[PDB]
Amino acid sequence: SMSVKKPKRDDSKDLALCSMILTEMETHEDAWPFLLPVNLKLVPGYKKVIKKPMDFSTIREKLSSGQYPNLETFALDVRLVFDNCETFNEDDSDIGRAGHNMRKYFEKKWTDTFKV
Ligand SMILES: CC(=O)NCCCC[C@H](N)C(=O)O
Image 1 (cartoon, rainbow, N blue to C red):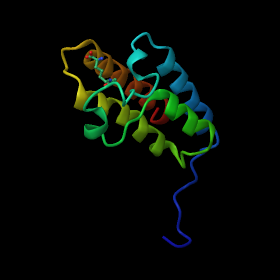
Image 2: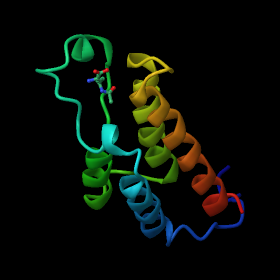
Image 3: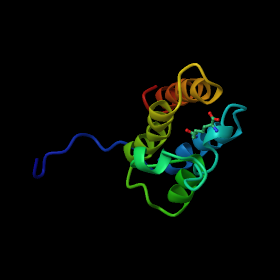
């Protein structure tokens, strides 16, 4: 509360660390469905259904331009990519399997990096 704070976590490396994680996401062989925005003119239903589209290039742009106030807002965008994927694609589809794989991949990195 006022004048009463938990010990200050060193947040000085977060930006570099999230960049690293994102670079690992981008180079994974199953990233291809998530590298660029879904093309809303060419994918019927997507615009109507998926209220907040998100993709790795957009996350990258937001990151490099200081648009994530903190760690968690970055994780929320990454998770949104996979929540969107789940909403639109069947689990038993190539893109549905990519999404599950990439989420698992992300959450382990997230844990190893920010929760020891
Ligand atoms: C990443 C994502 O959800 N893209 C939209 C779904 C694409 C559908 C794909 N072209 C298909 O044929 O199943």
